[PDB]
Length: 115
Length: 115
Length: 116
Length: 116
Ligand SMILES: [Cl-]
Ligand SMILES: [Mg+2]
Image (cartoon, rainbow over all chains, first blue to last red; front, side, top):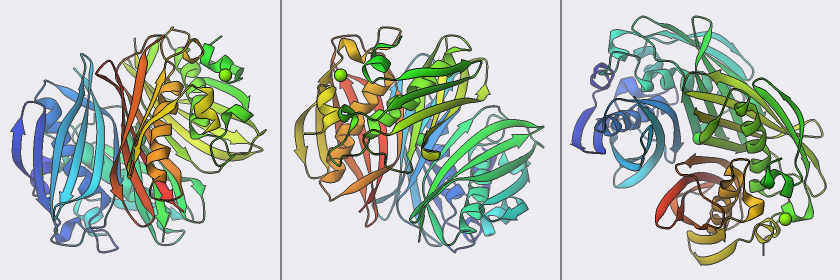
């Protein structure tokens, strides 16, 4: 996955209906304020979401929600754990927990359309 | 903004409560499927959202929603237009329309906490 | 008419392709412990307009909806939910619904349906 | 008790710090045109558990909520909304609420409040 590679993300776990993607907040991932850009954290969660959902077959994202809990500084190590919440014939929903230093720093919820 | 720069995003419009950010889907923005990664489109919308909201003062994102309408191929030119929906003393909400070839390809809705 | 809509006293004020306006009043049985309009009532109002607007394109079922609350509403307030189409695809569609009262935007609803 | 909750026949089954369980039955006045539980009723149920769970930490007001629908529910179905705390910060808090009936997950609600 080109975008994952460009952001330095690595797949740490993969299994039917689940996936864990990890990354570090690099200098090129910061916002003008000096903390991890919301787009980087979302990209991380979205990547785990994409991998987990696709273990069930071709699927395209329809709607996703991202809830931010704590700002992250440069160098922060982050892991996104995707878990299957619902699996229907035409759609599926996943929860992705973004964790750093053993605490939940963001929560992602997404639904895909199964091709 | 480091992340914006790293993704090749440019600010095309900026004004009180609004902003337009543009970008092109590069080779490093594609997913394993060959289309624009959901994280890239979100990063674009989130950047416009961040710029528009901060014209009102320091603000941090709390919750954001991204609705995807059409897959984008490599080279697609995309623009994210942020508009202020609500401005309260402690929070504010923005709508960000992601457009390509004159059509809405994604819709972003986000709320910030005003510092 | 829709049973739940009727029970809540909601009326369809306008309905056209891709759009709908539903109106209601915050009644005593729509209040929360605080004495203001319950979040569920405002959502029910928005959801009703959403359902009507989306159905103009053919049968559909709601998949995901977001409700953003901006202002509290008091008992007796007359409120409207104005739904407009944001996107119409072959298998899904998305709508924006503004909840307004006395010219003020009370809440914003965003929803996507799966087209049957 | 909460007026809107009462009007919908909802009962508080469990309440502890950061969590709550609200129960109800899909009544005739909770149905949509299709004859299934109206999306607004299921949201009202989830929102009620959300409000109760969040209030255990002190006064708060809902800011943004998401409702994801998975299965339709028929008239007469007994349903529960189970709220759990996902995050508690100084100014905001977030909860996950599962709507379940007959052991099946009917919907998923995610909500964030602003702490007063
Ligand atoms: Cl959402
Ligand atoms: Mg009644």
